[PDB]
Image (cartoon, rainbow, N blue to C red; front, side, top):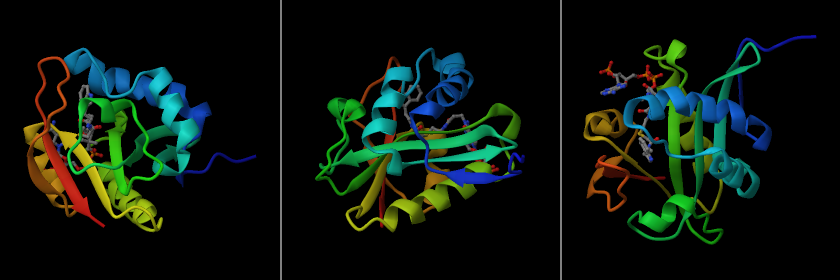
Length: 166
Ligand SMILES: CC(C)(COP(=O)(O)OP(=O)(O)OC[C@H]1O[C@@H](n2cnc3c(N)ncnc32)[C@H](O)[C@@H]1OP(=O)(O)O)[C@@H](O)C(=O)NCCC(=O)NCCSCC(=O)NCCc1c[nH]c2ccccc12
């Protein structure tokens, strides 16, 4: 009977298509590649949906974060496709906001809600991610500290690894 004006919930594999569509415009149209392809989105939403969060407006996904657990201090090429159940780090594989909903605090609201959501899970002691140099200041606003160049390479893109103690 009703499509909520705003809904925040963990994602399930049924949201994979919506997530990938956002990635097409958000990442692929810019650099030619993206953090998670359809199969990879489904992988993490199957293994660890509790490590994801999505913002729905009138029944449509407008922002998401997909993560998994990592168990090493630094991110590695292999960590891109792995979920370490025994790990203590919430690895945010991707964060994006639908192009028609940016610049209005949605990314910041979703990120803070995410940090509190996963930080609330006794097992998660830290959050890690990588971003392009221009987003470093942004993440620092949430308690993330620049942790040097990330070892992970994607095409010609280089990233700074960011760590947040929870
Ligand atoms: C960034 C985000 C989520 C903010 O949302 P919003 O617009 O709703 O945000 P707010 O309104 O809450 O705040 C906006 C703030 O963010 C700043 N900002 C936004 N875009 C900026 C930019 N390009 N450069 C500098 N500052 C910027 C604004 O300047 C502004 O600050 P000020 O107004 O105070 O200066 C939203 O713009 C978005 O979804 N963008 C596209 C996807 C993306 O990059 N995800 C983050 C990748 S970083 C995490 C990640 O996913 N890593 C994977 C790394 C990765 C793996 N494989 C790949 C393949 C290709 C590419 C990347 C990868």
